[PDB]
Image 1 (cartoon, helix red, strand yellow):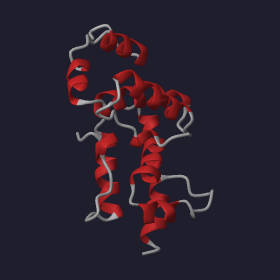
Image 2 (cartoon, chains in turn purple, red):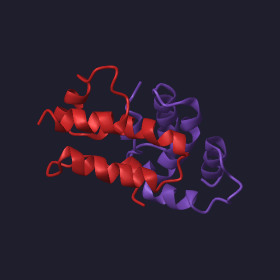
Image 3 (spheres, chains in turn orange, blue):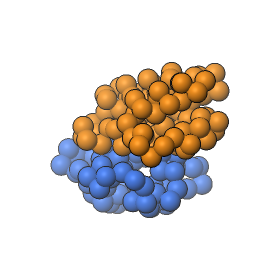
Length: 77
Length: 77
């Protein structure tokens, strides 16, 4: 699988293409299953494009899963 | 704390300076405590300079902790 910790959203990539890429790489990694979701969330925050990073930090505290953040972002495009 | 998933060894940084930087950022993150060590190991493998990446993958299967990998690398300089 790809090096998950190297995955960033590039300037010709959408957020969802980066999320899909990232998640596939995390799932193929040696991380424990319980580590996957928190890693994915941190990488969403840190490795998306700046405008998306800024949108993610507006999300309510009740949205905690990767899927909730994906929907939050996509539904605001 | 710093964005752990953005931390890479730069060309004027030693491995240990990167490990220390990385580990401080991981410890200050919201990751669950059990996720820290596997994240650190993956980032050692993925985010160090190529020569160090190549040295790390020679390590025996018995070396599993961050500290064991740090000693492995430093003791071979």
